Length: 352
Image (cartoon, rainbow, N blue to C red; front, top):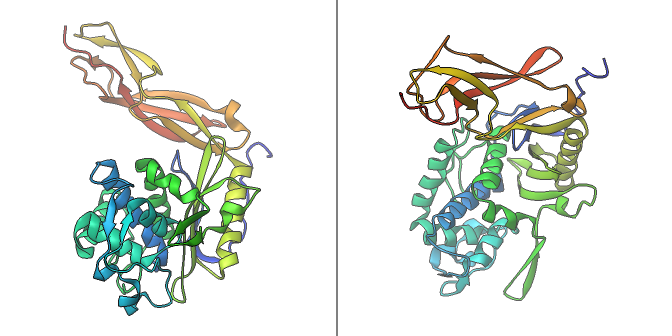
């Protein structure tokens, strides 16, 4: 009963949430996770993703200078009123490093416009790219209209979708992701602190991601933390205060590290199984996985994980191509299959 117990989830003071393992993708806990909500500033996570992808392809670098224009003039556009701004003025020449830090640490809205034009030519074009990555990531409940989150009646996202975007950031664009743990940056004589309070929380290892709020949206936070080793991502949307969005995320991440752990039972290229092959240049096929296997299981239960496999066909006949799928690996706890992954040919077997 103690071995097999399923932990109760804490009550979370928020309209929606999700908690997932970053490595495995497992949803440890969720409430209203696909409901469409106003993402507010969590939109800047996609802005930052596009910028991170552009830098990864080498289209520009952190030291490069961006000349500010009229659309990024903070007090030249009342759309920016009451919002967070770097106070960019036309003519300024600002290193990319300082503009992405305005975006990531400060949620500077004028910074988003400057980087958007620089990166994609116009805001409409950049927004096209945001939504192109919405499609490529396979997000079912997200649409962007702006580069910042302001002035967008038809923009939406979800606790699940925002957590997936967090994952993409960490996974796809890690040089861009590591900026999110920086607690302060200086721009134009003025020291600006990271809005994500949980960075200062000494009981956890939070290193991201993004914060957000409107009287529409309520209070939103996407957070990620480590213990090891294990990485968890939480998205809480429509929390009730600033204090607030942080306290509720803390409950989720702590609960997650307490009751669950992440195992990596098998790597790419490492042989899990061997099977005889007919017609081939070798007698046997080396069988395994084309993707590193990560599982989230109840904490403590690592020594109880049993792995086995099934084959799709009675016989294996050459030619066999690399990563050809030929079966399924079953991971089990307590006699029951908890996870499956494709069984693949690790090395191509040409015909004799």
